[PDB]
Picture (cartoon, rainbow, N blue to C red):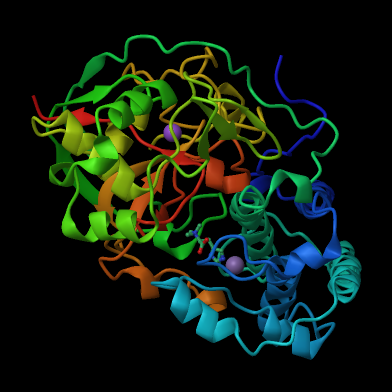
Length: 449
Ligand SMILES: C[N+](C)(C)[C@@H](Cc1cnc[nH]1)C(=O)O
Ligand SMILES: [Mn+2]
Ligand code: NA
């Protein structure tokens, strides 16, 4: 048994994006985000920015709606917006290098009332639904079709369901209410031995073809052949129990496992353990979305990139993280691979659970290479600076989606998490974050020999 009462619709091929199917997918995208945002009990909590590097929650309540409107205006499927001031106020978010830069940016913003932003959402929903009902869906949809703006808006909303869930997780438990049917994975369980598996080397082609019949973001496209040498990777994501051993061996107290930049981050934030653990009465509790529970020892540990690399430092002996090409080889092999959307059901993706799961519990989630949960459970960090593939081109609808972040200051992560939905659960999505940032994200370890 797994989570069932809250359901996320699978993504749809562009050749099957009929008006009726898209109506259902749109309604589901929006209702899911509504369920998440309604879990905040008190409206005053929307003026908190629980992550010090992101905007207050009120911004994210409006932003998904404003983005749909702004892109539909840009392709001229909408002749006017709903509230021009809000379309500007909620237009774009933030990716600051530090909390002081963000604090300076948000210091003098007059935010609307929570009820006014909910009213904006409800009006936007009805305006977009009417656009859908009054537009011909001439199959197939594609990147030069006006309806690309709608496809982009729905994936953007599902991405913000995921990133907003990480903000609500940073609120105190007394400030949020678990939605009916939210179901965590089973949590008792000591981890099994995490064996190193030889991944046979081969050649991969990274990227996505322009006429592939699936919505994707600009940075997904291009074509890059990479020869990948054989390498060893741990069959499981590193677990909470494995990371607890690192803590007990003074992992956060030993400079040689860190570097000057990551140690500085650790000291500045007085970090002694992963973000969502707390030590009390001699033992660690763990913060799931809405509840504190005993630390689930066999779940994948959730860390930022700095902490993943510090664990690699403790392992020593050339222990490292995979590259993007190495993850692709392990997850999809060397094959014109035809995505099968139904396979999303085989991994802890798309709200199969409302939490990470024990490594290996989902019995269909072993890739052919032998590695477990390459797809799903938690994103996994990669030692790969976010970068374009040959053939990359920004899209007119969102020219700065990815180009600003090809800056050697963002590391990549791939594969999707329990909370990931839409085309972000499939092969081509490329994800990236500053290395100090927290997501529903872990890692596995690699050695060359
Ligand atoms: C690709 N990530 C997940 C890093 C992006 C997704 C995104 C949201 N709005 C525009 N892009 C981010 O969170 O900034
Ligand atoms: Mn956004
Ligand atoms: Na994964």
